[PDB]
Image (cartoon, rainbow over all chains, first blue to last red; front, side, top):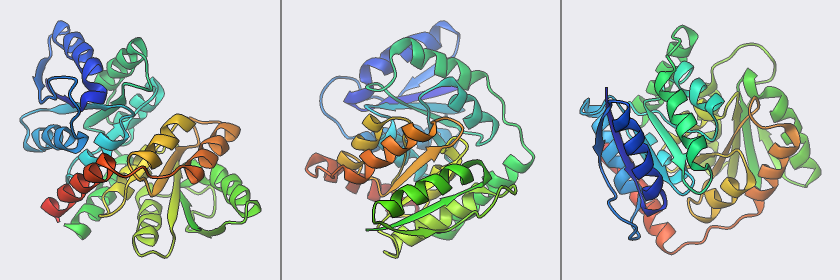
Length: 148
Length: 148
């Protein structure tokens, strides 16, 4: 499974740790940047990861900024993308089970390292539950079609 | 300001408490439903609140589901909407200061009542900081224009 990862400067250090974590677990990781601590704009990297997941270049993606909020909002502007900002493993599991999230969003200034790794672990293992949850995801698709 | 509020059945009881909280505070509250515990679909109510904020019928919105994730993803599909899932007041403050969030999303199964009221209090009081944050919000707007 190919994981796309991306961040602004606010999520760069956590991105480094998650990339190492994932590779060590045998995932193929595509790093979309940013590649340093210099101030940059979260939508640019949110977009890169979202478009890679949309195109199938990556199976899913992880985006990080100070809070995860900006980068996940940006990613959610792309049709077919469902980016979930999670601050605990319960949320991470429900994002997969109910929302079939294909992007996990994290906030480097909010969650500490080991917690963030717990969340990533949980998110990568959880499975979409279909049924009424598929019906609700379709209704998200209807909003996209409306504003398309 | 006029506050739009909406939920599925997973956020209905918290919605009831927040509606009461806001009115006691002097806010005009527009309740878009749901109006009971019957199973319903979060995108329908996410859409209502998002469209009310977009039209200027409400100045800001609050959306609630079990985790806040589904309803906020749905809301974020609407152009001009920036919905922030917050699990603490630090996130709530940054969502206004940096992301100029116009919708707050909450997870009734994640945050307890008093915490959720603290987050709402913080979110309503926080102020957009402009500058590079406006530049970044514009870049969110560019993604919307791309996929419009």
